[PDB]
Length: 142
Length: 170
Length: 139
Length: 153
Image (cartoon, helix red, strand yellow):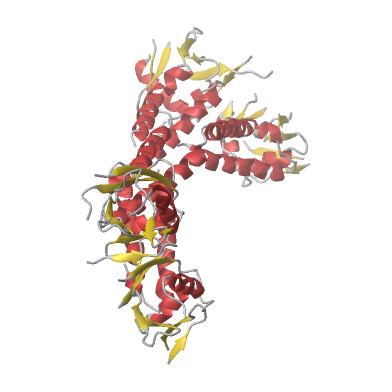
């Protein structure tokens, strides 16, 4: 019920929330407590997790059990939240890489189909001979 | 000392054509001018040019046997210097680029021959035109930032792989 | 209903700033009224979901990019209003207009790499010449 | 007397006696100078061995020592001797100084350095740094919205 986002945030959905993976779980508790009448505890594997641990590191280890618990001081039924797989966390990221990589090959492929390295070698090399003659004749050149 | 001057011109290749005034009638046999055009490669030595001209001018006469006339190359210094026939043509010209006129002396011919050393614009005409063309072809960017941003993203995904404890690689 | 973009980071909507909380969007609407919640479409394969007032404005609508509209419940009457979300071309435009201008401006202007390198060699080639001659050399 | 001059390229022009002009490379051995000189002089028949001596107290450099390394040691004496097997008196050839050998070389650098400044000054006076950064930047923001909207760009 927690989704990776195009940016580096995380969307959470349960009986809609935003968090940063570098925020501590205390922030999650703060947001959750604001939508309810209140201690929020996080178990995952099983073991509870300190509210001073980063959410990023938390759902990381939670991938072992594919999900994690949320229990509330008062209510009796616990809440379970599925954690993103690695691929789930890296979808938009690996996508951006795939596209940038392809963007590069196009850029490089153009450079090749234009003989751009010989063009630079030819140009730079002959600008050298031109500059060199100017020094030989005792003149200046653009 | 001859009223007609020689010119050597540049070519778009490494080669040079040498235009010379030959003061011999084409049917003369021994020793106002006739033209001679000569393509030479800048690494051919001066001694090679001598051999070239000697084929296009009549022999000299010493006693009852013909001789190939000595041909010698001179240039500026403010006086005049004799150049070694083992000198490459291109390097010879390169040195004479300031005096704008060098001398070619034919044995048995009192009046020498002077060649106009080409101007800078002329010596460099073809190259400078190719530069303009090549430069024009280039003018028809985001690469550095793009490849940099990519490798960084490659790194973060490798990182999440090890943290999430899985293998990666596309 | 409609929400639209501005060339500055600010955002304009109208009806019957990105970093502000939804609570603020609720808080200042009440200045134009006699509890305001927000909702949007949610896929998992449809659904409507209530968003925390602590959600940033800009961070919120970026999640609603795919469904080009979102709900908003006001008290009193169960007649929810829907707001237009500008499509990609509509939002990126004022940016894309600046990019094209800039990229064209960049087009209006490299021997640099060779110069620097060719210089370093010369600088190195003379530094050596000084030492071989046992001389100090300054520029 | 004789003179050995630096040329705009790495070569060396040598002038010595109706003086004779020569072009040699600093990386060639003195034997090459001997070969070139012997061709422009009469024999003795066999070729005359010519020996090069620079100052130290006046010693002969081997025919296998490079001309470059020969003249940089000759600068101490600021000239060097050439003797021909046969001719009684010797030739002395002024050798270039360090500022002489590096004139054209240092001259090229000044022009390049200045050219580099002009190229860089244009970059400054045109806010080049802010240009690409704003460009590279808001490009990524655009490429990001496409990822958000699930579209291409």
